[PDB]
Length: 333
Ligand SMILES: Nc1ncnc2c1ncn2[C@@H]1O[C@H](COP(=O)(O)OP(=O)(O)O)[C@@H](O)[C@H]1O
Ligand SMILES: N[C@@H](CSC(c1ccccc1)(c1ccccc1)c1ccccc1)C(=O)O
Ligand SMILES: [Mg+2]
Image 1 (cartoon, rainbow, N blue to C red):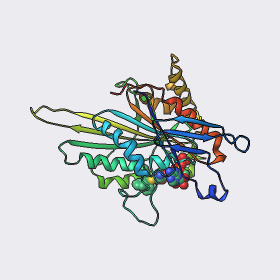
Image 2 (cartoon, rainbow, N blue to C red):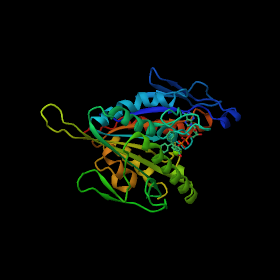
Image 3 (tube, rainbow, N blue to C red):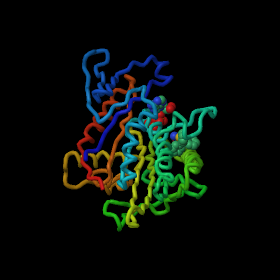
Image 4 (cartoon, rainbow, N blue to C red):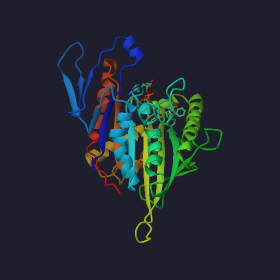
């Protein structure tokens, strides 16, 4: 199966409006096209146009991303496949907005209902909605690690010091897999446990940002949720499934400070060019993503872009990068 690639353009922000920014991006959700105006003052007609698996314009809301992209992927996780979604694009374009989301200010909504909530919390909410006493015995475990300068931090660890480091090893049980030694995996017994877990993770990240330069823009964030499902149907026979979903928020594409982003590009180039050796081992991120990139996990990429003329070169870089990645084949479960 080819990696599926979608584009999400964010709306203008107040500073862009204040600077009287013009748009250089047109999205056509129906034709699944994004068309970028490239000639500035000089050449009013030149464009580059790309077709993707889906295209989300500035008016797309969090709930539309969920319904279109995540729901189908989560149903596949529930069938016991492994899936990955990662966000790629320049700092400021909405990777974290998309993957995690934000809380609406002054208290207006519950987390399960917040319209600014992104992929991670909606996914956790749906896992419990879908599975709960609906016949299956099931458990859910989460982990959240971040890669910065090729060091690995555990945002969910009971340790009060976020700087305490994890270590990665090959997994002798699983050919393309790693063991993250020290990684706290929290059993989430029900939906009413979700928020406090995410909240404490976010507070550890805020600390991390005070400790390390340009932390949030240089970091890669790797949230994983594993679902163990058990069934005893018609004979009394017992049929076990395990689904895993990785939700990944990459370093800003404008970027050992950068080894993982660099190596991901070299890995994607190797896969599309079909070159014989693919350098997964040369970074922490690509070791973590090995199975998602030419392996047995179903992968989707959300490429995030700004609409503003100012960001022309990086917007074009992001679209070219993401477009070629459609050519990568995985073979799920
Ligand atoms: N689709 C969107 N709709 C509304 N605001 C958005 C959207 N995407 C991003 N933003 C806003 O733009 C700013 C940067 O988003 P952020 O998620 O921090 O980007 P990144 O993680 O790619 O650096 C934030 O203020 C965020 O609320
Ligand atoms: N993106 C925000 C956190 S948004 C987030 C969240 C979502 C996924 C993982 C961790 C936190 C949140 C913010 C603040 C307190 C708790 C949780 C969130 C936003 C909306 C609904 C549910 C969770 C940040 O970088 O701090
Ligand atoms: Mg971010």
